[PDB]
Image (cartoon, helix red, strand yellow):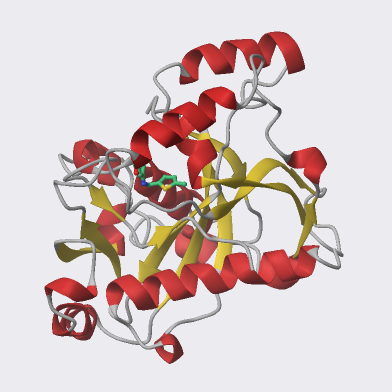
Length: 291
Ligand SMILES: Cc1ccc(CNc2cccc(C(=O)O)c2)s1
């Protein structure tokens, strides 16, 4: 799958909030463009003169992540984070010259991302009480991946000693996105586990943190909540469910061609980190069928 690469796969079935450290530093920001940040300002001004109701918003930037030696005690992951914006995204990753900026970054900084906003996304593998994952159909009128299948998530907005607060807002924001889009009560959801980080090679390498969340409702009760909001309660245009049994081979189905890259990352990491049984009991051939 050329349109998604794994930057990180978490150990132990995924990491809770308490085993993650963040470092939020202006050293983790995008570098100023070789010819000045004027190019981003020009693209923004042009866009507002066609859509004057658009507004900017701050975003987190992923610079890098380091995993501890496996089986160790203490914090297991460090996230190195800066700040970016929707405006900087439109002028870099979403720019037609995005591939030229990646080449210039390799040359100048030995880093394909050095000149890119790279806003951090979040997505969820959301499992029901009756063992399904939750999918959403994207509107055909949106800018990115129109009409494709997605999972719940989005792009959290800011606001280890400021670090711990940053880690809490990331985990809080995946739950809030599930409540806003799927119309579920907060109290039907587990604390999320981080499965890993996935890069969207169709959006110049920007990264999404991918999480596992369990709901205490069945698929049928999840569907009821989603629909009972009506058309204005959600950006998506439909909800559907796949048994966890059948998620194992999803990359061999006709659905795979309709999944947006960030939802591909969520399913690949769910299959590696929550599936793939390591032990003699869940490993047995009747429970884990060959081929
Ligand atoms: C900071 C974000 C990363 C990706 C986002 C999704 N929305 C989007 C994508 C591509 C163009 C546009 C537009 O408004 O042109 C919107 S939001």
